[PDB]
Every structure is written in structure tokens, then in C-alpha cells.
Image (cartoon, one colour):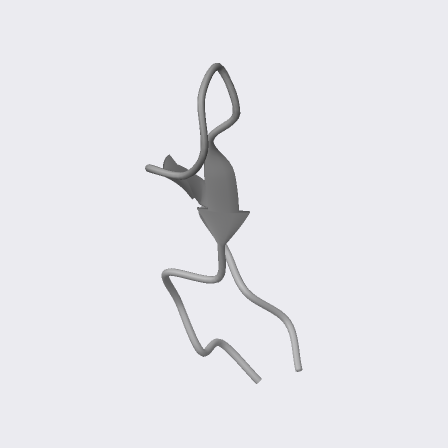
Length: 25
């Protein structure tokens, strides 16, 4: 699996959550 743009999503206090925003083979 190779993403392309991990966008830090929202999470606990002062702590974002970068998840995979692209499913590029």
C-alpha cells in the first residue's frame, strides 16, 4: 500500500492524526 498525502486529521489535545488520504498502489 502506498498513500500519497497523509493529512493530519483531528485527535486528542494538541495531537493530530495523519491518516492515508490516497490508495495509490
